[PDB]
Length: 168
Ligand SMILES: CCNC(=O)Nc1cccc2c1[nH]c1ncnc(NN3C(=O)CCC3(C)C)c12
Image (cartoon, rainbow, N blue to C red; front, side, top):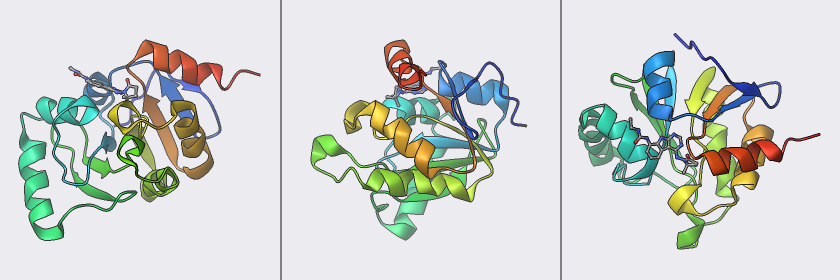
């Protein structure tokens, strides 16, 4: 029921909290939780592994059936699947993996998917093993997303770096 609490407002429509997205989803009951997916929807580590584990692997089973129909997602693309016990829906979004030579401009396309949903609980995209600059990723989010986004950033050092970038 979108019961967000304890977020710091960064812009008109972007909020941030130093929190685990899994625990946030369980307490907030969001309409949409965003997954930092790969193109095969193989949820083996990071946010993706944690979300899948919290669904007792139901997310992975569903993801495999979607991929059977779709083939791989495109970088910058997404799909809407069930949110299982975490949310009404999970929006699986593929940001570019710059560590693997993919183009950082597809981070714009990745965040543009958020505009198809009124309110989202989301992680930072193209971070972790994807290797993009995290301050840049937050800037792309702020400049691209116009619906309401609640960013959960679990790593304290990264959270602090991000919030510093909005200091007046
Ligand atoms: C109940 C058990 N919960 C868990 O294992 N959760 C869990 C595991 C691993 C990773 C995350 C996580 N939860 C998160 N929430 C938000 N961002 C996350 N990852 N990131 C950061 O922290 C900075 C940027 C990015 C790399 C995306 C994670």
